[PDB]
Amino acid sequence: SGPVPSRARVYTDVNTHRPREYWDYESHVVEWGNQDDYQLVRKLGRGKYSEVFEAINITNNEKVVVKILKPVKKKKIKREIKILENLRGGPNIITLADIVKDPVSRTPALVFEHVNNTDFKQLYQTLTDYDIRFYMYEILKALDYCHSMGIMHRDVKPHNVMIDHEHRKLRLIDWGLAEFYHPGQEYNVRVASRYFKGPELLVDYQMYDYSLDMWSLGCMLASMIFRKEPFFHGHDNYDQLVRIAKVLGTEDLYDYIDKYNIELDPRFNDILGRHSRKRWERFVHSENQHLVSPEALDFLDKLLRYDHQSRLTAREAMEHPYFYTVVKDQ
């Protein structure tokens, strides 16, 4: 008959109670800043959709990050801009400062607050048990904020978390794939990076919600505590589900597709097979011992569920025993 509907357990109708202007991004009017305000200093990186530069605001000699957009549908640019403006001032959310027309690409360039960051390459190297708890807690603040505001990030992974370790300061960035949550809406499943895609995305269940972000956060945590980056390292979208299935087992997977009456791709038949659910202990060795605790495993288990309804919400996560010691400190 087709798949069973679903709604977010939390923040279900927040957008419905807003004025349409809040989520009706297609009708947002960009008000352009002055592109001569900013002088480019050096290239920071290349994205799928942007070139990223360090720049100076000459009017006030402050350091900024400029994201020059590749050509993309104006719809998508209005979205990102709208989401960024709705979220401004929220905890650990990157601040958009200005928006300008690049004279050379004739495309938008978003201008962000500068964040002096340590590379997750050289960072997930040096992190103590406490650091991970602290930063995950900081990420959860950002995710509970943006979910409470009717927005799912849809691209949570280590690249999108900026940490200034010297200042113990964290920002969730790259809001380019983020969407407004509406009960009943069927989303594109071609979001997130492979290693971070929820099972919902992999079996093509379009009526997903904020809980997607919680899976992704599970993948990050797994890779930090067990020191295997990325944790679920599939070579393509089908191999990804099989890698998950090999840890979480096939019984719950098939239970999941059953509950939601999901029609599984015939390609998946010959490859999923039959796998038991593994105990987390099998990833604990002497190099990662000091980051793994019973608290940490209980928490990770509660994030990494096929059934998106059963995963913790950002808010429930934040009150898990794993964070008791960081909560007391603040």
Image: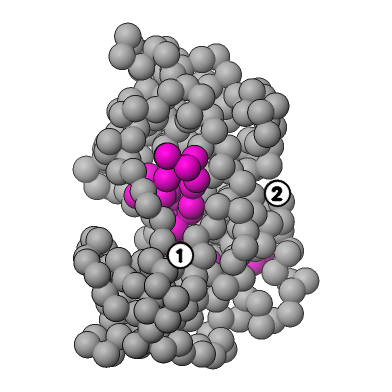
Percent of width and height locating residue 227 = 33, 25
**Residue type (three-letter) at the residue carrying disc 1:** Glu
Numbered mark located on residue 254 in the image: none
Q: Going 22% across and 87% down the picture, which residue do you hit?
A: 104
For the residues marked 1 and 2, what is the alpha-carbon distance in whole angstroms? 33 Å
Percent of width and height locating residue 187 = 50, 65
Percent of width and height locating residue 82 = 55, 76
Q: Residues within 10 Å of mark 2 (few under 14, many from 20)?
A: few
Say which of 271 and 201 sits in front.
201
**Residue type (three-letter) at the residue carrying disc 2:** Arg
Numbered mark located on residue 113 in the image: 1
Q: Is residue 164 above or below residue 81?
A: above
Describe residue 31's horizontal placement relative to residue 312 as left or right.
Answer: left
Q: Which residue is mark 2?
A: 9
User: Helix, strand or loop at disc 2?
Assistant: loop
User: CB atoms at circles 1 and 2 under 8 Å apart?
Assistant: no
Choose the circle earlier in sequence order: 1 or 2. 2
Say which of 113 and 158 sits in front.
113
Is residue 176 part of the magenta span, yes or no? yes
Q: Is residue 146 visible?
A: yes
Tell me the magenta residue range.
154-183
Say which of 149 and 261 sits in front.
149
Mark 1 or 2: in front is: 1
Q: Going 55% across and 52% down the picture, which residue do you hit?
A: 92
Is residue 33 part of the magenta span, yes or no? no
Describe residue 50's horizontal placement relative to residue 316 as left or right.
Answer: left
User: Helix, strand or loop at disc 1?
Assistant: strand
Q: Going 41% across and 56% down the picture, which residue do you hit?
A: 115
